[PDB]
Length: 169
Length: 169
Ligand SMILES: [Mn+2]
Ligand SMILES: [Mn+2]
Ligand SMILES: [Mn+2]
Ligand SMILES: [Mn+2]
Image 1 (cartoon, helix red, strand yellow):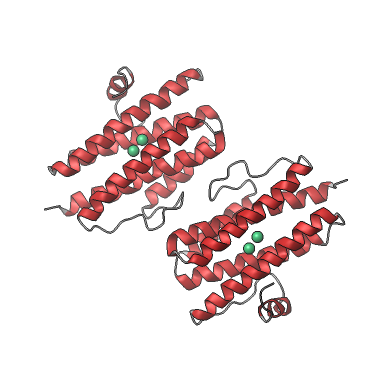
Image 2 (tube, rainbow over the protein chains, first blue to last red):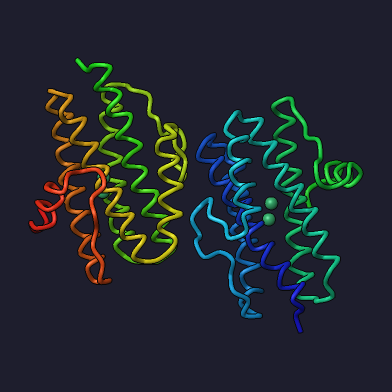
């Protein structure tokens, strides 16, 4: 059976995937870099994956309004606003924000992964995490094309180096 | 030729139609009342009409990001946020917000209409205004079905009474 702590996790990650989807849709509409469109689609997939677990356990969905920018947990509302403002400044700032979101997601997925023994919850979280590593590699390579790079904020320097020095999974 | 004042008008109204489109899309996603979907479509039409004038005179479009909730003029950013927060409380509050937006739009269209002699600008503004009267009648009738009604905020009491006591145009 699912624990209250495990429920709290799925609730947070349901909106964390939405944060990434929403920022990326917003930055695509701004800068029309295909990367944002492509990855926003992948985030929609991830949102769906978490929703399927929510439904499986009949947990109330925090997403009561699918509209871009709308969140139940204000942690994500504040992150949405701060990150779109940053990302509006330049193509490089928007790509840095992509890398930032993925950085936070990988750190948060690690957090929740380490609090559960449920194999169906782990498979989804591991798959989400593999996705976020792929996204991080894609955003950084793009920052490289602009003559830029990324400094990690949430995961360790060492984890960041392992991600970017390997090819996409 | 177009005046700087006339340009300022089209710039404001381009984002004012977006405000209505965006709040209505957001409230539809919340409450799934068809009225919001239907009228949001009409606002997309109105947005397009203003854009066609912007392009005709090669005025820079204030809409640099079509994403819901994004505005160049912060008057509309603040209105977007305040109105979605209000509209999230209940179906009746959301319908009151529809009526409010239309109220403001009719008042603002009257303002700009009275500052121009350009027939192509007037035709569009008159057509927009006829649209907003239709929308206001639809939102109020819906509030009536909920046992509610609307108090005008921007247009006069007398103008509000003329609108709602006539049938849709
Ligand atoms: Mn994801
Ligand atoms: Mn991602
Ligand atoms: Mn309109
Ligand atoms: Mn309207």
